[PDB]
Every structure is written in structure tokens, then in C-alpha cells.
Length: 156
Ligand code: NA
Image (spheres, rainbow, N blue to C red):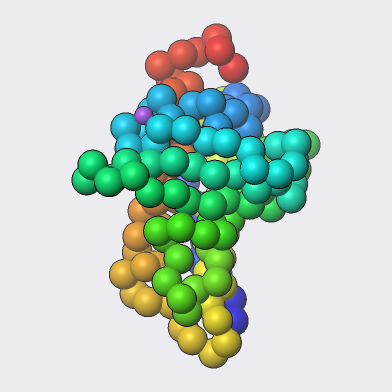
């Protein structure tokens, strides 16, 4: 089964810029996140369908996460990707998607929804903590991306 959660948020950065930064996740993430060290394309051209491998060190031990790029709606400032392998997936959970949608803000800010789709195996329901870890993680990347942009205004 699949279980969906939606969270709403705002940013001072206009959505067009956040979106650009969002598309450049491979580049930025290793810089902003201490534990992320690299992102490599395994197969695909960076578009939807692409499979990526993230290398991390956590508590000094190297680990791998596997991502799939789900869709892109540039006109709509939407960037979606799923965690398809690695540390975030318990056996009941087959995948976890993170979707980010941005809309025009009142103050030349961005209005955005973070959607988490938790796909479990069979009738299993999501673990409470995994869900909590996943929400924090989604929100975390968004903030990190926002931070990079504030730090560097003209890059995007
Ligand atoms: Na790093």
C-alpha cells in the first residue's frame, strides 16, 4: 500500500530560483550536508527515470543510498524523487517518495507543498518513527537548498 502526507511551507526565495537549485541537488547536496559526500548517476541522463547513488559517511561508516528521479514539471516548479534503496528502507517499505511543489508567493517568496508518499509492502502500514524520520529528512533538504540559495543569491 501507499500512504501520503502533505506539509505546506514558505520561503523568502522566489520559486523560480528554488526550483533551479532543486534541479542541481547532485552538485549542492554534498557541499551543504556534511555526511553526504557524492552523488553519481548510475543510469539515465538526470531526467525522470534516472537512478543515482549517494555516498555518505555516518558515524564514520560509509553507506549508500539509492534514489530514483520520479518526475519534473519545470513549468510547475516541481521536483520529485524517491528513495529506492539504502539506509532509509525497512523491508516492509519498498520505497519512499519526496515531492516538492512550489508556487508564487505574496512577497516574491515561494509557496510550497512537501509531499511524502510512503509505499509499504502489502498491507503493512508505515512505522511511526520511519515516517517521522522521513518528514524531517524531506524538510531538511528543502531548508538546505534554501540556505545555499540565500548564501549565494546570483548563482540562481
Ligand atoms: Na559533504
